[PDB]
Length: 50
DNA sequence: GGATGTATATATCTGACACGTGCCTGGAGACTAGGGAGTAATCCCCTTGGCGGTTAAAACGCGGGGGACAGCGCGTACGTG
Image 1 (tube, rainbow, N blue to C red):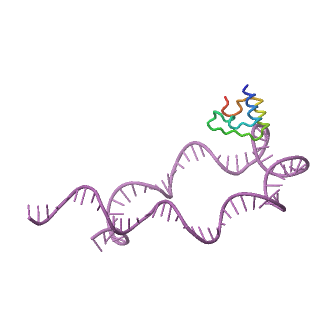
Image 2 (cartoon, rainbow, N blue to C red):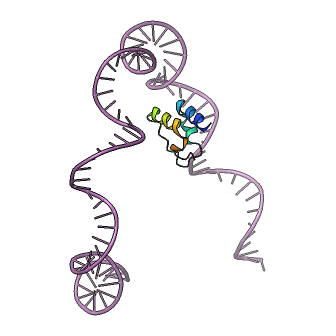
Image 3 (cartoon, rainbow, N blue to C red):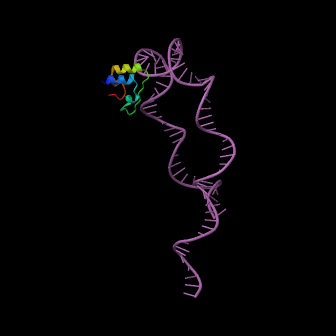
């Protein structure tokens, strides 16, 4: 479910939702396919996701 | 009996407001052309994540000595009347 919601947030870009509870909130959505591969691998690759 | 402090009434200042007037500059309406929005193609530059190898620059430790800083004197230059 976490992988699915991260894929939905990246593919339909949701910077406000991708920030969410992060204090810094420094999310880079350049190289969309790289972030999609990271979401397909593990959600813990993203910052403030564990 | 003379002199003194307070209270309401009228004339004058003083900025603000109602009215008047010109006039000119902004607004209403119509028309047009062109500037900018949108589309497609092509090619070069940038992004994020990796790798390998060189090597010169960065980091760390330590001695020491040069310089920052504190204290004291003095005399003169500036404050003060």
